[PDB]
Image (cartoon, rainbow over all chains, first blue to last red; front, side, top):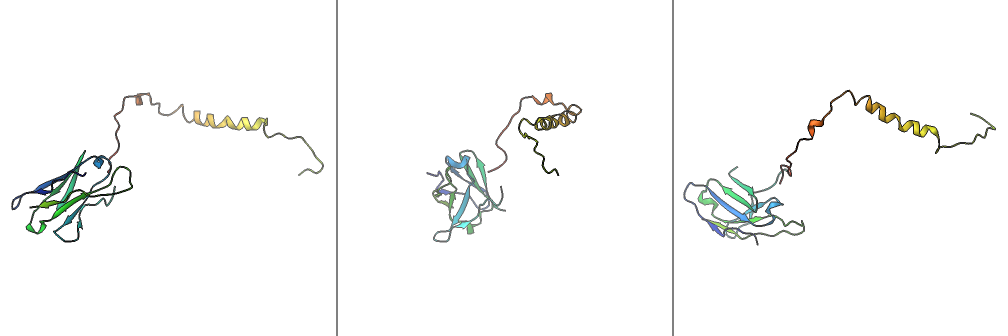
Length: 98
Length: 53
C-alpha cells in the first residue's frame, strides 16, 4: 500500500511537500497525477530522460514538492510508479491539496 | 599449379599454426614494456550504482 497523506495544508503563498512512501521507491522512478474532483487526472511528473512542480527521491520515499499554490490547484494528487517485477502498476491514495 | 603431384599434407601438426600464435605476444611485449606500468592502481576504490533512476 503506497503511503501518502490523503490531504496536506498550506497558506496563501507558501510551498508544500507531499511524501509518497513505501518499498519499491528504491528501484523505480515515480510519476504523479492531478485529479481535480471529477476531472481527468492530469500528468505532471515524468522521466523524459534517464517548472513549478517537482518530486525529490529519498530512499523509501519520493517527496512531491509544489511551489506556488494558487487556489487553482486544489485537487486530489496521486503518486504512481511500478513494483520491482515490472509487470503491474497501481496507484496510491489521493492527496487533497488544501 | 602442379598437375600429377600428390604430396601428403597436414594442417594440424602443421608447424605454421603454432608459429602464428607466437607473433601476437611479441608485438604486445614490444608495444607493452615501453609504456605506463600501473601498480599504483591497486589502491582501494569506493564504488556505487551510478547516477540514474
